[PDB]
Image (cartoon, rainbow, N blue to C red; front, side, top):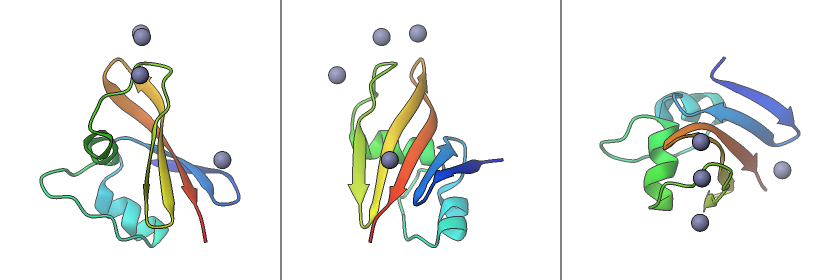
Length: 84
Ligand SMILES: [Zn+2]
Ligand SMILES: [Zn+2]
Ligand SMILES: [Zn+2]
Ligand SMILES: [Zn+2]
């Protein structure tokens, strides 16, 4: 699967998940031109590639996206929290 829940309002999302897929699953409104995946989305939004083990976040609307797992410079897994 491209994502899994871990707790109320909190999920792990594979970097390869399409932004459009994420919006369909989660009822969100993310958009970014010339970028198709959630890995590309978060990397672009952060503006810098995190070190392995470094877990910066980007907030947008009621969502917080965290770089949960890097494999070299590839963003493998995002953590997503939803707020009210
Ligand atoms: Zn949490
Ligand atoms: Zn740093
Ligand atoms: Zn390192
Ligand atoms: Zn390494």
